[PDB]
Length: 355
Ligand SMILES: Nc1ncnc2c1ncn2[C@@H]1O[C@H](COP(=O)(O)OP(=O)(O)OP(=O)(O)O)[C@@H](O)[C@H]1O
Ligand SMILES: Cc1oncc1/C(O)=C(\C#N)C(=O)Nc1ccc(S(=O)(=O)c2ccc(Cl)cc2)cc1
Ligand SMILES: [Mg+2]
Ligand SMILES: [Mg+2]
Ligand SMILES: [Zn+2]
Image (cartoon, rainbow, N blue to C red; front, side, top):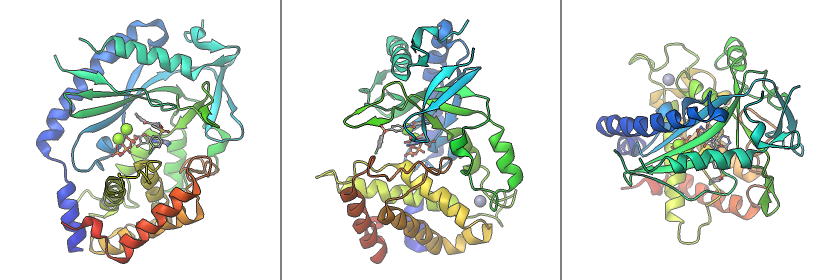
């Protein structure tokens, strides 16, 4: 109620910073797209705006933007890596502009990402000050910082207008919330592959790509009610986005405060985003997200997240057999540690949110 509302007030974005940040991002992104379009291998590149800024659930400051530099790849053939469900080798069906990145029959993610990064790096010294952050192992992101303030994650994304892979067949369980009609329309849209490599023991399988549905996530968050007029008038202001923002802030704050021994380094905002989509599936009616019930609605979000930690299971919303909380990705000790901290917070009405 009052405490949660006070937090949300604190997390609001300034209309001014949104405006200035937008222009800075546009300038940088427009430059890089222009350069990339010169290269024969990136001719068809195009922009897709994704993540929390464009979903209107960015908190505190508009200082982190996410964009896909998408590139259509006709006639694409996938081989699932190691029954991982989310990671794939990319092949082609019988002049391919991507010829140069092939290793045997296979398009190398690492080869193609490296050139992508190169060109952008090579272009970053040309009206604003932009610096490129260190490459994170196995990440799809090329991360820039503008004016020592605004981070922009750029991922290359292959775009396939084929039907989604078989691994997604039982995902996107929105039928009871957003409708069967909408699920069908959504699954007619493209899917993306980004050069995030599957973990291989201590390293990465460096030719693998991973599915991305960032475009669908954005569409859902910006058209998120059972009612088509959800959040379009003062009588239908649900608390869905408020609950996602609080879950994000809860995790951010816990990560900050536990930074001395880095217990929570393996947890990310996408974990709480995923958990939140599952709670939307469980609670499909707008009446289950009434502004008057902010407290209860947030609790529903927290207790589902707690269940996910304790069962060490958090299914990718689109790929059910991809477990974001597997031992492969996050060790048991870390999940047990966050479980305890979230329980403490829940049991004491979130002291971490006190001013
Ligand atoms: N592990 C992942 N699997 C699939 N998609 C992911 C994953 N991590 C991030 N993404 C996609 O990348 C987008 C941007 O990621 P990012 O970490 O910037 O989070 P965000 O949703 O923008 O939230 P915020 O940036 O406020 O923490 C996500 O919204 C999601 O669509
Ligand atoms: C841009 C961008 O624009 N649209 C989407 C998108 C994007 O960032 C992704 C997509 N799709 C995407 O998958 N990101 C992504 C980035 C990093 C990593 S990690 O494994 O390095 C990592 C694990 C845990 C932690 Cl705590 C921190 C890092 C995994 C995925
Ligand atoms: Mg982001
Ligand atoms: Mg990001
Ligand atoms: Zn709403």
